Amino acid sequence: ERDFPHHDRICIVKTHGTRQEGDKPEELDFSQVSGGVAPAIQEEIPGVELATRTTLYGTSKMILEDNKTYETKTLLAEPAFLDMFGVELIAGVRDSALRDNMTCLISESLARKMGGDVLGKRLRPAESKSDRAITIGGVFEDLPHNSSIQADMLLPITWMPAESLNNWIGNDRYIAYVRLRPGVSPESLDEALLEMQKRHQDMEVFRKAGVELHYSLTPFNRLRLEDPTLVNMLRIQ
Amino acid sequence: DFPHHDRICIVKTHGLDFSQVSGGVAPAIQEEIPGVELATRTTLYGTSKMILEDNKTYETKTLLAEPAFLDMFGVELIAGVRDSALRDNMTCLISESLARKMGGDVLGKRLRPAESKSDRAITIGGVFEDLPHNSSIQADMLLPITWMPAESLNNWIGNDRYIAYVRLRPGVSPESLDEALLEMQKRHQDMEVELHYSLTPFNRLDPTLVNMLRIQQ
Image (cartoon, rainbow over all chains, first blue to last red; front, side, top):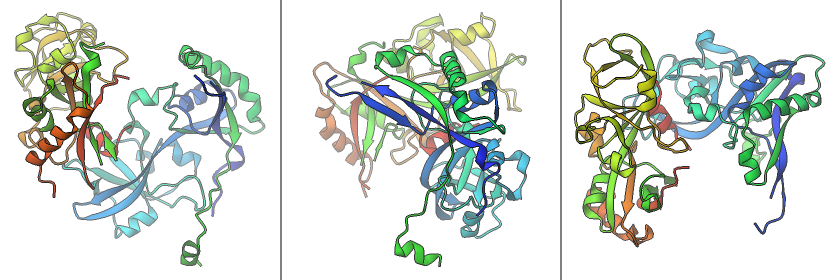
């Protein structure tokens, strides 16, 4: 399995801090962030080559062309996801990818399960009573296995409400990936991150809840092994 | 805060829990359930571009609503006739902020969906005072819920794109109504996962894939 491009230089944004009505003080440790953070980092923080955001929808059922039903794991992503993770399309137009809200990308395995030749076909949620549908605009090479980044289907992040995308308080449902330029240590950026946080985040809301937190970059280790049961393991020997 | 905000609930579904319902629920609740002062329904259209008098284009968050929406949420009309509001499918109400953005004096002007090749138009029948900022309820433009087809509106199964708001009478607990709701459900939907209606207090302060898909442009 491939390494991601420049993998030695990819970090994720973590959040650390403390909270506090009868209950003892809590140390806060998050691996996900509010929507607003990733774009701001790319714009504002020196030494950042690229930043991008994802949010996992999860697994749900999709019906293809009004017939067969497929369980699909859906991830919401930016066009930059393709660059950040070196994702190549087997079919469809790369420039187009993940720009139109009514279109999706499907993994090579999923396309195969669907019977192949899926480009241009239409998908909708299994329980939908509408003829509105999502069009398959591309097919992407399966993402590396035994990795934290997992998706059967990719949809544009713009599906999310503008309020979420621009949020700095709570709703920490996004993973923010940051690629640094060579020679930049993640730790060096703590102060700038703070400056950025102060610019965008109303701090009042936190003090009211007795919360202090801050962001820091940590190197990204993708490894997440598939649950190693005999049943799982046997299937791939 | 909305009027009697302490007594406002929304309809949730329980089996798995959801805060939206099929089109038919709200009217039935008002009709058949004792302890209920008022009930109304809305569905979010989404954000789209509207063209004003064949000139400038404005991005507009659009919400479909009933006239009772004005009562339930205490919405004052800055301009136009309240009694007329949201009666006619071919008219809309516009927020003060949008009206201002639009250069003002917008009463009677005509709007068309940008991407539309027809010349049919919606007319601005009123301007409403901006809704509270902190709320889950947001709209630049209000359109009559009767834009939706009968098949949607009267439906009890699926297509749960509606938010149903209920104002209880004083001294009635939400919990108290679970039984009457169940009776209501049996009458309206043949029951043949288990799903049931319940009321939870509305807190003006998590999208499903179907929900998101519906409002995408």
